[PDB]
Amino acid sequence: LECPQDWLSHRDKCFHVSQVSNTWEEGLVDCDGKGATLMLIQDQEELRFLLDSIKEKYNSFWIGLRYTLPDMNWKWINGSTLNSDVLKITGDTENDSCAAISGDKVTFESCNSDNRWICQKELY
Amino acid sequence: LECPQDWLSHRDKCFHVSQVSNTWEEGLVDCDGKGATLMLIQDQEELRFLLDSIKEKYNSFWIGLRYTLPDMNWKWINGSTLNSDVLKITGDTENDSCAAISGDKVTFESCNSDNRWICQKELY
Image (cartoon, rainbow over all chains, first blue to last red; front, side, top):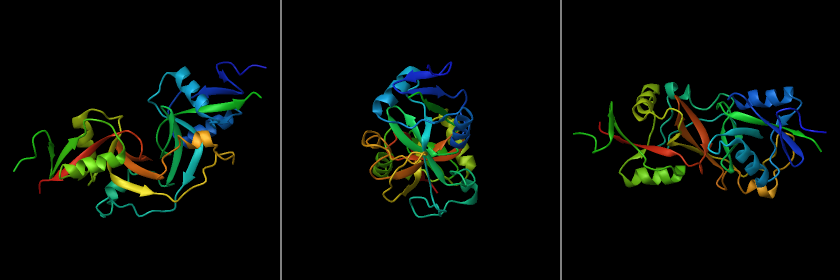
């Protein structure tokens, strides 16, 4: 019983890092199609192991954590409303944020960001 | 009437990009201390001009837009709760997300990210 070919083995899990960057949803669907899921982090060690095997400590990798927000009237810190032109490129219609590993932290980022992603399989 | 020394001039505004990366709040306080504010984007042209004068189209720069979230019970996409060890490095206690320019989009990112920031002054 080994991890599939080209998957990284660690403790009870197999990991695979995506070839391309894309949105969170594209990652979630990609992992599904592999009989896998986006990475669920059990502890910081796991996070450190991955990041040190990949050698991209700055980059962001999508993981399996997301929240949605109700519809929001976005305003600048001075109280002025964002105008039409800027709203066209601000966040996503879905108003979701998605977790990504970066460094040795987990940060939430708009889900339409293009990031690589990490899929996981449980061996045991 | 010129922009201060070392500020970038554009249309009715002067811009200054921070020397170091730090959290959103440190940016907001830094701009204040300069008689300035974090960048408020009037339109995509402005965004393009900055990004093309700086020549860091990938990087994230804080701007003057932020939202807070109520306290949240974070769960993984499979419904399992994040454990203690992972919660220690996931987002920020404040549970805020902050806007940053990247590429030619505005993305929301956890406010404890270390990004450079852009301050603005209005000349007219």
